[PDB]
Length: 133
Image 1: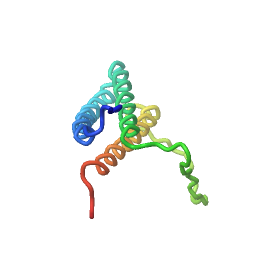
Image 2 (image 1 turned 180 degrees about the vertical axis):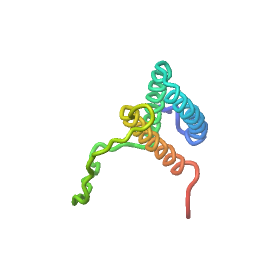
Image 3 (image 1 turned 135 degrees about the vertical axis):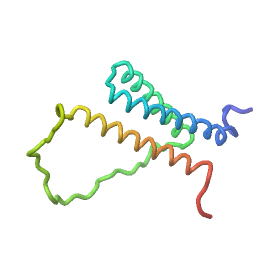
Image 4 (image 1 turned 45 degrees about the vertical axis):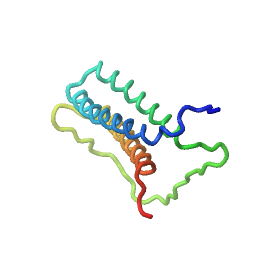
């Protein structure tokens, strides 16, 4: 009769999965600070593979619980006028050297964690506890 295995066990399985991603996120943040300050090669490879596996599993989780449509989808345009221009004259770098290669990776990883945090917060808020009547 039944074709699918998951029908009732989905709301009780998300809580444990969310707690697992939370403990992994905290351990990944501590290992990220220790790997960037101490500088390593093995820790960066393991961090990239673990981050890609958590991102792929998180995308599959949101694609499994939340349905997807083929026809439709809204596109963004964002209005612009053009006010105030930014110009570079003094890079500034006191200490030992200059930071440019580490800044790009720090902003890219920080943006990926911000989107990852908003995604986990949206699934937690939508399923589990509801706000207002």
